[PDB]
Structures are given as C-alpha cells and as structure tokens.
Image (spheres, rainbow, N blue to C red):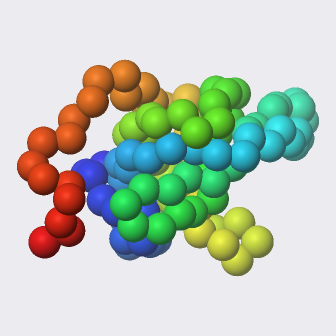
Amino acid sequence: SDLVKIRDVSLSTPYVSVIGKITGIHKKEYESDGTTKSVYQGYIEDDTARIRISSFGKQLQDSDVVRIDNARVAQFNGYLSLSVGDSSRIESVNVNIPLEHHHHHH
C-alpha cells in the first residue's frame, strides 16, 4: 500500500496508494451477490500518465484532486485499473504543496 506512480501500477502490487485528479465521471450498475450496487468509473492523471479507476458506493468529482490509499489493482476488459472498495480510504487535497522550483524539470 506504498505510494507509487500510475505507470508503476501492476498486479505485482495488489495494494497501492496513488494521488492525482479524476476526470469524466461515469455511473454504472452491476449485480453484487444478487443485490444491485452502483459504481462510479472515470480517468485519473498525474505527473506521469493516466489510468482507469472504479469506485464502489463512493462518488467521485470531476477534476478533483484526491489521494487514494490501499487501492486494489484489477484487470477489466484487458485494461488495468484501480478499484476503491469500502476498505480503502480517500483523502481530498485542499492544501497546496509546491516547494522547489517547478520552472525546470531537472
């Protein structure tokens, strides 16, 4: 459940923590144990690349910067994505943290 980059997401790390902004919120429903449950899907990006995400029960906000802890990696439609269950934790980032000179990538 350590902090890793989106491009570093793989099955080798079932539990991982990521931070970025979620965009394009999509709503979908599926049958869970015979009970219909709502799940939100969207895309998240950071300083590296972007990946698909899926949240069960918890809602997501467009272009909202949040941090996901204990995320579960899974393959959907042959595509890797992070699944946020009720056991995972989501923390919003309302405090700025620039530091250092972002003018040069070096």
* Residue 32 visible, this orientation: no
x 29%, y 24%: residue: 95
* Residue 45 visible, this orientation: yes
x 37%, y 60%: residue: 47
Among all residues in the image, which is located at the extreme bottom? 78
Among all residues in the image, which is located at the extreme top? 94
- Horizontal side of residue 95 vs 42, given as left or right: left
Among all residues in the image, which is located at the extreme left? 100
Quadrant in the picture for the C terminus: bottom left
- Horizontal side of residue 83 vs 48, given as left or right: right
Q: Nearer the viewer, residue 85 or 44?
A: 44
- How many numbered badges does the structure rendering display? 0
x 42%, y 71%: residue: 7
Rendered position, 41 above or below 39 = below
- Horizontal side of residue 10 vs 27, given as left or right: left
Q: Position of residue 63 (x, y in %)?
A: 58, 39
Q: Nearer the viewer, residue 95 or 39?
A: 95
Rendered position, 82 above or below 22 = below
Q: Nearer the viewer, residue 35 or 76?
A: 76
x 45%, y 35%: residue: 66
Instruction: Give the quarter of the image for residue 98.
Output: top left
Rendered position, 46 above or below 39 = below
Q: Position of residue 60 (x, y in %)?
A: 64, 32
Q: Position of residue 32 (x, y in %)?
A: 81, 39
Among all residues in the image, which is located at the extreme front? 103
Instruction: Give the quarter of the image for residue 85.
Output: top right
